[PDB]
Amino acid sequence: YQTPTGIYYEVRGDTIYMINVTSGEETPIHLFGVNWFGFETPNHVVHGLWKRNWEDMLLQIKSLGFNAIRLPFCTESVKPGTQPIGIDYSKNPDLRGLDSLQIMEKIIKKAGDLGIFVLLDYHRIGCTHIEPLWYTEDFSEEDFINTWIEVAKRFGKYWNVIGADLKNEPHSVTSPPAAYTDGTGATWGMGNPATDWNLAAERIGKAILKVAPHWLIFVEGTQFTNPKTDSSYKWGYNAWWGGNLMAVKDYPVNLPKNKLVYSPHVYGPDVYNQPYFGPAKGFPDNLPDIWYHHFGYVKLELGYSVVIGEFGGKYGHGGDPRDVIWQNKLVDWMIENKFCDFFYWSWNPDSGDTGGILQDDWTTIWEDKYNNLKRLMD
Ligand SMILES: [Zn+2]
Ligand SMILES: [Zn+2]
Ligand SMILES: [Zn+2]
Ligand SMILES: [Zn+2]
Ligand SMILES: [Zn+2]
Ligand SMILES: [Zn+2]
Ligand SMILES: [Zn+2]
Ligand SMILES: [Zn+2]
Image (cartoon, rainbow, N blue to C red):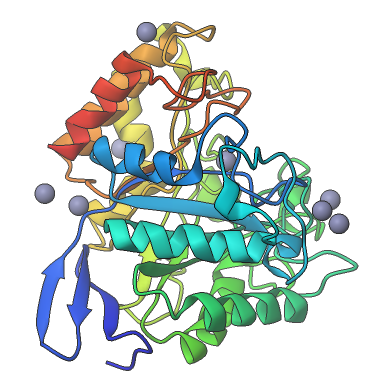
């Protein structure tokens, strides 16, 4: 167990372990997580620091029973010198004069004092859009990897950083079948290095494990994988961005079994009006089998650690009424099948189709939404 902190994380079966290498103590951990976003935006800092103090926010997250944060970032936020925008330095006087990296470091050190796990998520290459692929004509794979290497060297020193969510939401920007071969979108198992996320995750993960051997590597799904795989299931074309893990069975990512975590995204009627959200398609009793095929079998049949990295919705608040039913159904199903490690989207209220756990006052929570979610925390 090599580690620069004394702590080494690893997967055993479908369970995540935290190992203290000096003393030999080791425990399984849950991830009861939330996303707290903003470092992937042009403000270059988690949102909500106009109305709240950053440390009060971490304390509140903890008081609600969460023990983990997924922290989205974009390339510019993790380069030295990038200035954060929108902080009220009267509520946050200890942030005055800090750059976004210093703020990230301060927040992660504090989460660690509070016993909060951090998962780092390279959410966008620019700070405006999630790209479909892990590069761009102006930012190469080599650049993407070098950024993760400099993130891993800097943040690998914080004991509570559990690892790297390689690239948020690989997806497509045209329909199949062109999306499989037109080079504009992520694929999986096409046998084409320009677009295959399964092969990229191997290359990117290996590079990170060289400098942070103690980290977990979280790999999301794609949107479309390969014609064979997607056409083999009736809703095979209707998986979310980062939400199609159908190609794992035939094309497993070839990263060490004790390091690899699979991390699908899954959403409800508030995010997209999927055909399968018709009561006249089986809703909501049809859901379990759809989740099972899109990603659940990766745990339930193949035995891997599967940590849902995003799910959420308005839960009836200025949104689709079916959302309340959908989050209730999805949480029942995660309980019944022991998907106990997750990250909810999001802590922040300022997410247009999902809202968050906090209300728009950035202070009060959606009680009912939270009470449903809290069933996962036992
Ligand atoms: Zn768990
Ligand atoms: Zn437990
Ligand atoms: Zn900027
Ligand atoms: Zn800029
Ligand atoms: Zn762009
Ligand atoms: Zn089935
Ligand atoms: Zn998302
Ligand atoms: Zn309500």
